[PDB]
Amino acid sequence: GYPLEMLLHSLRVFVVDPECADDALGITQYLIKRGDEYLKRTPSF
């Protein structure tokens, strides 16, 4: 739902940090992979 969007949009900041980029990238991979059923209902996001 909205927690998915909030978490993705907030981790997008750490994803491009030379430190702790891998933690954010792992969480982002997991979220995009698991919330596939939702992301197909919100293509505009």
Image (tube, rainbow, N blue to C red):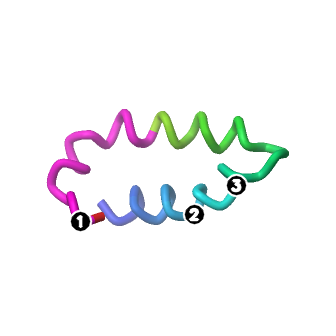
Q: Earlier in the sequence, mark 3 or mark 1?
A: 3
Residue 2 percent location from the top left of the image: 35, 65
Judging from the image, what secondary structure is the residue with disc 2 in?
helix
Residue beneath disc 2: 10
Q: Earlier in the sequence, mark 2 or mark 1?
A: 2
Asked if marks 2 and 1 touch (Cβ < 8 Å), the reply is no
Please report the residue visible at 22 percent of the width from the left and 49 percent of the height from the top: 38
Residue 14 is marked as 3
Q: CA distance from mark 3 to mark 1?
A: 23 Å
Please report the residue visible at 26 percent of the width from the left and 40 percent of the height from the top: 36
Please report the residue visible at 60 percent of the width from the left and 56 percent of the height from the top: 11
Asked if marks 3 and 1 touch (Cβ < 8 Å), the reply is no
Q: CA distance from mark 3 to mark 2?
A: 8 Å
Please report the residue visible at 49 percent of the width from the left and 56 percent of the height from the top: 8
User: Closer to the camera, 2 or 20?
Assistant: 20
Residue beneath disc 1: 44
The span shown in magenta is: 31-44
Q: CA distance from mark 2 to mark 1?
A: 17 Å
Q: Is 31 on the left or on the right of 12, as rendered?
A: left
Residue 32 percent location from the top left of the image: 39, 41
Q: Residue furthest right?
A: 19
